[PDB]
Amino acid sequence: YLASLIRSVVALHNLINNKIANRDAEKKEG
Amino acid sequence: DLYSRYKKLQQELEFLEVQEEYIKDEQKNLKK
Amino acid sequence: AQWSILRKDIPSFERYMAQLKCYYFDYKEQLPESAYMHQLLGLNLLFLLSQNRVAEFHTELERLPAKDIQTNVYIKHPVSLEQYLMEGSYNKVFLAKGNIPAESYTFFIDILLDTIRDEIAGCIEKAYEKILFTEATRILFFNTPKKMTDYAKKRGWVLGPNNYYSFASQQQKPEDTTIPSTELAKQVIEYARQLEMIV
Amino acid sequence: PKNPDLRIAQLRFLLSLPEHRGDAAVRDELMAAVRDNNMAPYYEALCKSLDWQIDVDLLNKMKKANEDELKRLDEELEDAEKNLGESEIRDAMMAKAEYLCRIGDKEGALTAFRKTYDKTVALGHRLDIVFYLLRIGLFYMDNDLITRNTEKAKSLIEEGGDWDRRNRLKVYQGLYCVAIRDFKQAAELFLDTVSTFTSYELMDYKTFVTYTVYVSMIALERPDLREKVIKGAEILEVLHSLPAVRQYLFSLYECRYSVFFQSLAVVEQEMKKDWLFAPHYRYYVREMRIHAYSQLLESYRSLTLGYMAEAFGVGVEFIDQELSRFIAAGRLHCKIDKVNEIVETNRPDSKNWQYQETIKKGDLLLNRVQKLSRVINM
Amino acid sequence: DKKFHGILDQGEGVLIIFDEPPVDKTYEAALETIQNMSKVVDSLYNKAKKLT
Amino acid sequence: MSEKKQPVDEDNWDDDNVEDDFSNQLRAELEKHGYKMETS
Amino acid sequence: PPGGGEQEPPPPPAPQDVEMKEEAATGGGSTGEADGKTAAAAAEHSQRELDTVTLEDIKEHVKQLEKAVSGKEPRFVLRALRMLPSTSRRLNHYVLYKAVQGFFTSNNATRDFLLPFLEEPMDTEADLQFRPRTGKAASTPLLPEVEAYLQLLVVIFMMNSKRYKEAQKISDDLMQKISTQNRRALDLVAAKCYYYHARVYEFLDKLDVVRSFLHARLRTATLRHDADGQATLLNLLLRNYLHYSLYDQAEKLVSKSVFPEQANNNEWARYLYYTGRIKAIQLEYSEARRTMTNALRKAPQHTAVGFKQTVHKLLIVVELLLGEIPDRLQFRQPSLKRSLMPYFLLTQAVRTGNLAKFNQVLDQFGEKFQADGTYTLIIRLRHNVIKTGVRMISLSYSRISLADIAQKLQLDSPEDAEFIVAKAIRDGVIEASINHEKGYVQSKEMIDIYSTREPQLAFHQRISFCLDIHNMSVKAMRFP
């Protein structure tokens, strides 16, 4: 519960930080 | 065109299987 | 179908009944009502209860809108029968055997009661060691029958000094349960494998 | 006007809903109703009570007189005297609405309160109007007004003045006892019992002590209940006045269970005479009956229910049926028995308790990141 | 009142004395992190809700 | 987000756990539950 | 005209302007993302499709006179769009014809010209390169055309429009789906056309005609690869075969196509509803109620939606087929008032040992039970009338005399109390056992559920799921 959960949430934090920074550079190209 | 497109997809597919291989290999060897 | 149940034939009775059911599987069904249908289904509904297809029993009952409750004792007889198998009511099955609106349903009910007797047997074939002949009358059935000779020759249960002997059906349970040591050591390995190896 | 007013709302309940109880409430309400000029609310109350009597038109012209006598005051005032805000127009027109809260219905009073609320600038006059809305929402138990203005009292007012909020602390948990919140929020801020005089803002004292001692033995069993209510001394003064309430306390704490039921029998029947009463009585007793069982099964692990037949009350089959209903309820963690007649208990260990909490909270967060992973990635 | 670590029996009239487990700390520190991790998923829940 | 699976569509405020437990067991709880003692 | 007619000019033009620029930017955006970066699952495809379920059904119902949806057909009657000048010619025509329909009156669709609004919009050089445009702008004019509901020579306007649109879909399915995969669009297009073609076959005769074609679309599905195509068609193919009250369920028991394997939280939700309906009727109760529980907690994000009222209705029945019952009506709705009163008063009688009240419920509320598709409860819930208390007793007591349990279960005979408890343990209600010597029904062993390897099993389940989220997240997060 302490190692598998917390490592997943950190990688889940890297989801949203990627997908926000992906499309906000995409929609602001032009 | 219908045959020439088919081989060009194979050659690229063989290539970018090699490039994903050693980058996965290099990233392992880079951690040391 | 009437000839199939009269001649005591198991695979052929369901063979003709399926094609009969395929003919009530008619897509364009104008089809004025052949008055033998409801007891024909009741033959199949009682037969398929008898071979312990209870999951197929209730999924067949979908096709009747109001004949289950309003009328039609031919279909009302197995579903009242199956209701009696539910709660605790073994004996009402064996008492309401002697009431059939149709022909006697004899090739269905004798296999039907025999697959009730082994459940009473499989309850009483446990490691609970000894009972007497009056428990055979209560639990199994039948004050002095040929059936006590039947279970004497088929099974044990021999009447000794006014006592039946049922042997211990008890298991031995050889357990260590640390013997999941290889598979538990295996189970740890794919943990660290799936953490690593994708680099 | 509003200050001794809440006893009337007790006699509105007590006369009406127990239909057998129609003897003594009307004896000291009707003589109080011909007093105090109470004219608008009692028409429906006279329907459920004895049908009619002609004092209606007597005080109708008398309620019209004092309506008109002060209406002509503040209309001449606003046409001659030219101050605003908290002026003489203010305190005359709040005297009209306080004439309405004492005499009329709520509706003319509340719209005059909203008429005069935006004419104020001082928070002290604002909060005294919010005192009036909270009390008239407590008259007619209307749960819509009281939820709003308490937030107005917290957020919009009481970042300013001070120690007119303890008057409404007793009103925050007056809401919680008329709600089903008989558990912790009531007993937590009832615990400051240093408010004595039976005022409008402190509606009674001795019954307030009985309110905070009934609700107190559900919030906590022994995380030092005995310091806050038993080693407490200012509470111990006035329960020395009431012998039955004190006996109800010390029977439970000093483990006298047979006299505890006789005390609890009086409490439930005495609870019947209350107007915030509907959440209590079917829930209060059954929570305390299972409260006494749980600590009694503690310190034993091989109890016999024949020992419940005299140390506890009587009724061998009565303990048997009531434990059976409570074990099947998912509470009262023990295992009743037949012919051995031994009430064996089973309580979990540390590890058997901790493993259950982690598997409940584990599947909660697992389900929580199930759904979150499906919202992302299309 | 927790002055003593034992238990009684009515069916035996017999007092039994046992001890207490002090090893609660690891599971106790475990499930408090789940209360923390429940709030950070709620923090990422409305972060994805506020903007996709 | 329809699924086209729609086509048809303290008084009792927090009571239903306590109500599913007991409903009508002579809720006055005194005339038998406290009046055992004349039978014993 | 002075009351409502002066507020008639404001409703066309702003839905003519900014609602038009929705699919203008989306259909432009979906096309270029079909051209480059063709894996556009993380794009505006989904939420626009979430809009076409929600928004455009409530954005417009009629075909929107003064040329908002009645103008769409003179708007897209003339679309060449074939070469880069032919697009830039029509991009000038996107400026021109929308301005004319915003200013003046084009061809006004007075609910009757729908087949010349299917030929000539499809004619005048309309492309199969813009097959999402033809796919969307044929499926979206179903919705003014069905929801008029006048049904006077409009059933064939439905019928021709679907067969036109699906022949365009077939022409995609055989000819050059070059990096496009319109199945993402054309799944719900195949659904929305056949929700109402099912409704057409509700007003008239049976809908096995749909199912033979729906096998054929599922035959051409699952062969290419499954990207929601097998998922959407499977719930559709299951629904009529469940809607028919014939035998009908062994066809689904042999239906070994159980895997969509990912369904965007919404197909998988109601898929678990229909297979829970199946496993409940063939007496697999314990597996049914836990996947009904999984279906209930999977899509609650709705507003009094009615199928949530349906899955909540079945799940309390199957747990009354297992003895236990939770609180149910604590989330009362504007529509749950009708559905709480039978079932709460039902389980009121189930928990008691009363039967004359229970039959009074059946005579009172049989019509609703027959309306809900749950005839079968009376033959199966009378079983658990005796099985509720014997589970309750075996949970409460520990070692009961079978002589005493007969009066407690009001069984009126001590001798068959062996038989019910035999039925309970053989079917596995309680793990207790009978001493057939002096009346004992003794319970289990002492609780040993920490030092007997059982905490490792649950701990392995939570490893195998949580780090599986981790690996699925890392692959899904980095596209660039």
Image: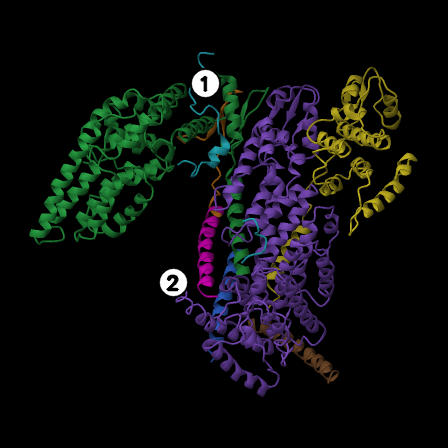
Chain colours: A blue, B brown, C yellow, D green, E orange, F cyan, G purple
Task: Return the x and y of residue G458 as percentages of the image width and height.
Answer: 60, 47
| Extent of the magenta region | E27-52
- Say which amino acid is labelled 1: Lys
Which label was assigned to residue F32? Answer: 1
Q: Quadrant of the C terminus of chain D?
A: bottom right
User: Does the residue at mark 2 contact the one at mark 1 (Cβ under 8 Å)?
Assistant: no
Q: Of B5 and C186, which appears nearest the observer?
A: B5
Chain label for disc 1: F
Spatial CA span between label 2 and label 1:
72 Å
Task: Return the x and y of residue G350 as percentages of the image width and height.
Answer: 58, 32
- The residue under the point 38% across, 65% down is G2
The residue where tag 2 is placed is G3
Callout 1: helix, strand or loop? loop
Q: Is residue D163 above or below residue C138?
A: below
Q: Of E35 and G328, which appears nearest the observer?
A: G328
Q: Is residue G454 left or right of residue D215?
A: right
Q: Quadrant of the N terminus of chain D?
A: top left
Callout 2: helix, strand or loop? loop
Q: Is residue G61 visible?
A: yes
Mark in front: 2 vs 1? 2
Task: Return the x and y of residue G196 as percentages of the image width and height.
Answer: 62, 59
